[PDB]
Length: 51
Length: 51
Length: 445
Image (cartoon, rainbow over all chains, first blue to last red; front, side):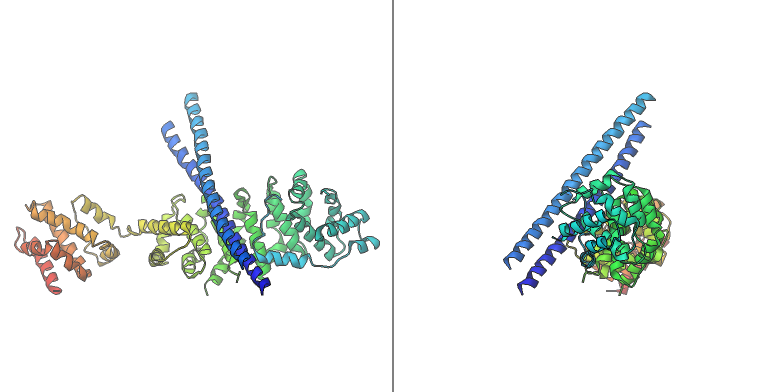
């Protein structure tokens, strides 16, 4: 029935929402890691030049 | 049926929006990295002048 | 209202639906004078205002039934309504603001949280976890207090109930959302290690794959810190090598790419002495063939495939040097060889055996290129050049012995004529090696 159909649709939207959530979380984590890495590299080069 | 199909289309659109948000997050991470590198560079120049 | 997580899993939804479905009358408790009449009235009104004005009035009043609870169902319903108000769209950030105003107000709440039965230790812990990492309020006190909780200890360590386990895990991850608050999590990670290894072992055998995915997500979040990733593989080696193997059999690419990125973060150059980890993993764990099959596999996600190729390249980086094939590559590129048992040892030859032919035997072509260039041009044999051409002769001999299909190229490379033309040389040793390669070519015709 259409009730279980709508439940299936909401389930699909739920799975998509979960995928998007995990994607956003991974995006934030990768952003943090990239920030730390870039900061470390820039600090290394700057320390080299300054030294 | 059409409601679920529209929910699927909106789900794909939400996925693409999540990807775009991830890209914007990456660009923002690069920008923050550039800012931190700028601050570290100014600090290194100030330290060099102080030395 | 502001940063409300844990709305994803249907387990928390069913749990919240089961807890909020309890039948209790605050008016009956007010008539029996079980608690503060004003607080009971505000609660009775808030119940009808929920199930279907601003907050802060019932905030202080709820503490009266919180710090002191004569009934278990009363405190359970209180914590349930609290957590429901935390995720409420009507109130939302307002409630958070009420938590943001007084930092010590949530202290006693967290102190009264997670006690007695597992049912009452759920909602209170959920609200506490929600507030702890919420927006601007961050304290190591609440984290340390929740970490030392024996009530949530058995809840997280329960292999029986999947609901409580997934709840405790998701709460751990939500609390680990802030890396700065994950330090104690890195300190208390010893207890989480058991459930992680248990989930890893259970991985090898509906929504039941979400819990392990969240656990791996927590592992990857802990892998964000190179310090926590430094003692990662230095703790449990058994569960470490069980990552990619179980990831290959894993249907979804989520937990798979999670374990992949986690192992990659473990072997990352950002980690000190991470080369030995990937080395042992590719040695005693047979990660070479797994990475090869993964490279031959397909992935829907771009990040997953990119991390896959990156991990494969990273592995192949230190895989080529064991047994270093780059040592012979240096001699080949510089067109100057020396005395080493690279082609003498069957093992060393077997290590680079798979790398002998990639595209149209490019490595073999470059290997025969030196001899060919020493054939059509040069071909004055004295000292170095002679022993180099001889070593190349023996190496190409062992190579042809290993690879039967390497003959067809030698005929089109003009090496078939040059090898036979090397029968008569200035040195008897060079002629011996050339005759050995001749008999080798006579082995398969």
